[PDB]
Image 1: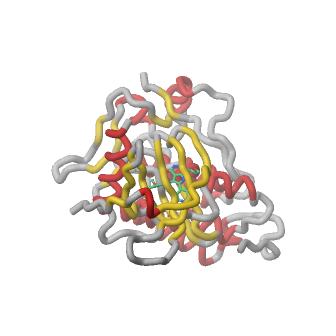
Image 2: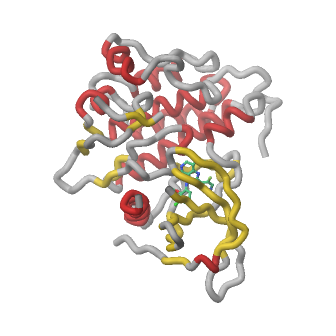
Image 3: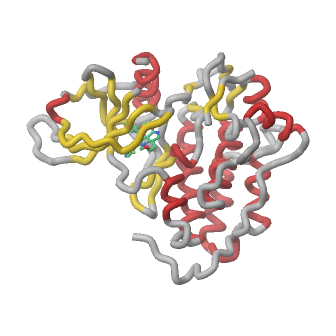
Length: 292
Ligand SMILES: COCC[C@H]1CNC(=O)c2c1[nH]c(-c1ccncc1F)c2Nc1cccc(Cl)c1OC
């Protein structure tokens, strides 16, 4: 059962703006619980009220048992707007992190992040949840060795006798969506596997924009012609074939998140065999459009 903890605005202090975009506005602060005096660093989101409360319901529904690689909602705050509260991730989003530390990320970190995103997505698949927005921008970095999936804005829960979600005319990310989602607005856990492949391609290219220069309306025709995202220079054939298996026309032929945990975990045990990065031993660490 989903339960929300209504937190008072007087409990939050030192609110500073982290960023803004399609997600709305994300801030950072210090949550002092009532009675307790432990200053917990937290993040606050804003944007209309109908949309942010759907996100809170989705996050609260999948909170028990919970997964270490999935962001969990601490509670909500009722100021002039409805705000979401979660544990702060000090190192920000992974898309910016891979673009900032281009020359310091080793093969072990890239493969472990792929394992962790697949562990989080497999947990969401078990809780009948289709994320519908898996991208490097929606992956946060708690510490360089630990990542979490975020932004349950487009996420939808599936009923017991429901294996797919049909969207209406809302804005959606075309360059991360599967071909069936662009053509027929159909969203399954296998459509999230396509987005997982695009997210893996983003990490392997250190934050390259997918299909750069190509407009969103030309993507369906490009994917029907057999064209896919290119092989990143650091990827061996085994890593690139996983990405290409995530982008197959038949959604059931694509890999499963439980299979991607095993495949990338095997690769993480011998990382230099599967990714070729210069000076790997020396390294050390401490969009949306209307469909038609
Ligand atoms: C600043 O924007 C980065 C990407 C942005 C993209 N979309 C997000 O949803 C989000 C982002 N940052 C953080 C975030 C979280 C935790 N610590 C730091 C951070 F920045 C997000 N989650 C988030 C923020 C506040 C409350 C809740 Cl319940 C959240 O989970 C949905």
